[PDB]
Amino acid sequence: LALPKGKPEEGGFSAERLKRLDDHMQTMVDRGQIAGGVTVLARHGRVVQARAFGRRVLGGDPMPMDAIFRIRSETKPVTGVAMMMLYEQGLWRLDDPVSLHIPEFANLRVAKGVDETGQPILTPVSRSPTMRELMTHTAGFAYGLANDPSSPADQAYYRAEVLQSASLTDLVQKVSGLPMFAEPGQLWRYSVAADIQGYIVEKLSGQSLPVFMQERIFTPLGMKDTAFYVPEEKQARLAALYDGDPATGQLVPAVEGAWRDVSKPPAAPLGGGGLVSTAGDFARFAQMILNKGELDGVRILKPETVALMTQNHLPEGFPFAAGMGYGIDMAVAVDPAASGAPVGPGTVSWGGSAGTWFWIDPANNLFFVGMIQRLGGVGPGLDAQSRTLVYQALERPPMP
Ligand code: NA
Ligand code: NA
Ligand code: NA
Ligand code: NA
């Protein structure tokens, strides 16, 4: 699994109590909640638990350890590293207006409310969002997958097919002429911001996003299976994506259509959602963050840059639990005691709509990668469950 192996007690875990995570994963397969999955738990640079469960596809063969997964929104922290590499080269600053780097954003308008004909009343945006706000989902851009007529801006991005564009130039031109959810800096709201960050990687680097991520991240870290598509020779390791249908609530093939397909290179590669990866590949990415920018003698970020990314960038003012802030393209647990969560302060995490999850806990020097392909609801449960089955198994000193 191209990362050092160890007994649980070398990570500081009870073997007996870690079996409870193994057991919960098997109970989730047995009771038909998921076809299968892969989990990786590492502490002090050594993998202490690495296990495959159930099946790749529902009828067929067992889940291999190097199964390939749609990681969806969990691509966002990878785009953040790409963006912070361009930061170290001086090509953009957090205080820059996004419109310095995307001039069409000069024409941004905001939905104030609706008139009697159910049309948004549109005002020119007060000012450009900042790059800091783009990296934090506080730029006021709308969400791209909600046909919600109570949020005009989201309705318009959905109707404009923002995420199913012909190119990243297209995506960004559409966004520039479409209503914003809100003025920049007003609230945190999950948005297309990482998909826009992707255009900025391309504009600033002179390379397409998939080339820039390959040369600067995946090849240097040995993330051999991480890409915006699954080449023909690897299609046999792809986990299949299952849903729960109404009535019987049992494992059904999922339908998503065209633009989500991972068999061909995508027209508009999504910095917020397009990557496939393996548990092993994502584990290497997680350890590079714990090492503050370096893996196996390969340095891709300065430690100051990793430290910046993994702090809360949300203003004092600030919809997602108590003690919970947000860094550069990641959630951060500023004060997890406030929500009774077991992770250490400074823990960074995220997850994907296909039910993959991870967290990196610098204070406890550990991380956890959870891989399934199950739409809506159950994936987040496994995340919270894993943490419990993980932090109950963890034995540390009282030394403060
Ligand atoms: Na580790
Ligand atoms: Na606009
Ligand atoms: Na932490
Ligand atoms: Na994961």
Image (cartoon, rainbow, N blue to C red):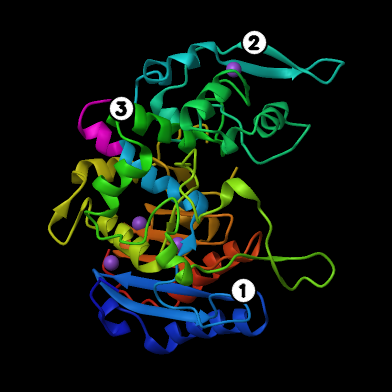
Across and down, in percent, residue 207 comes to 31, 34
What span is colored magenta in the figure?
84-93
Residue at the image point whose x is 58% and y is 75% from the top: 57
Label 1 vs label 3: CA separation? 41 Å
Dot 3: element: helix
Residue at which label 1 appears: 34
Give percent across and percent down for residue 9: 29, 84
- Callout 1 amino acid: Ile
Toward the bottom, the furthest residue is: 16
**189 left or right, relative to 9:** right
Q: Residue at the spot x=22%, y=50% of the render?
A: 293
- The percent coordinates of residue 260 (x first, y second) are 57, 50
Q: What amino acid type should be assigned to the residue bearing mark 3?
A: Leu
Q: Which is nearer the N-term, disc 1 or disc 2?
A: 1
User: Which of the two labelled residues, at mark 1 and mark 3, occupies the earlier sequence position?
Assistant: 1
Q: In this view, does 128 lie above or below 22?
A: above
Q: In terms of image quadrants, where is residue 358?
A: bottom left
373 within the magenta span: no
Q: Distance between the residues labelled 1 and 2?
A: 46 Å
Report helix, strand or loop for mark 2.
strand
Callout in the foreground (1, 2)? 1
Q: Nearer the viewer, residue 124 or 397?
A: 124
Local crowd size for mark 3, using a 10 Å CA cut-off: few (<14), some (14–19), many (≥20): few
Residue 332 appears in the picture as rendered? no
Which residue lies under the disc numbered 2?
123
**Label for residue 204?**
3
Q: Say which mark, if any, is on residue 77.
A: none
Mark 2 or mark 3, which has the lower sequence index?
Answer: 2
